[PDB]
Length: 47
Length: 122
Image 1 (cartoon, rainbow over the protein chains, first blue to last red):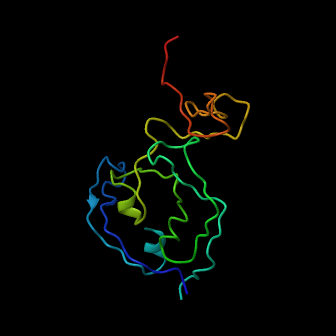
Image 2: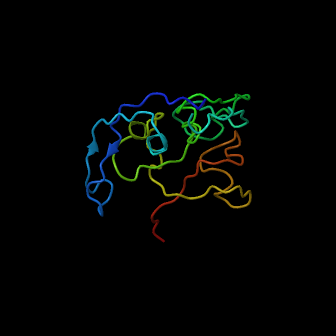
Image 3: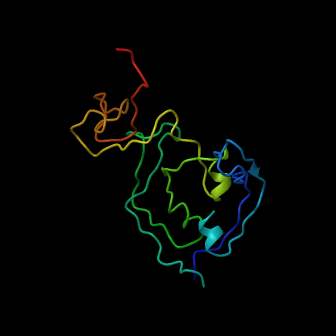
């Protein structure tokens, strides 16, 4: 028994890393909804 | 079977915002003992950034919630920079918070710093 996988989410919160060198706003647009499931380490932690 | 749910969290550290707007100072509650558990991603996420967490937004205008898949967050850090608020009782700023007040007008040992101006003119 592991703490429940549970839902994903609806997301306005990810911009892409678009302009790489440039700052977080100095260029990039919110990456539209990607609803990331409960799978393995990454989108468990990296979310 | 993932990394185990493990045991659930008994706690001495609960945090309860009295007035959900006014931040810090003896407007607050740290309640009676409540035991967090082994349940889900949530109680295993809002465990790691409990209510009162310190996080930033360095890139996108997006709110915290809409990315990390947790919680609700309104941007902190307005009009300041990142400075420790010391346990020190002696120094002026690091002991009692600026306008945070006991009924004597000073804060107790506390937090919620303020201060500063880029300049006054001599």
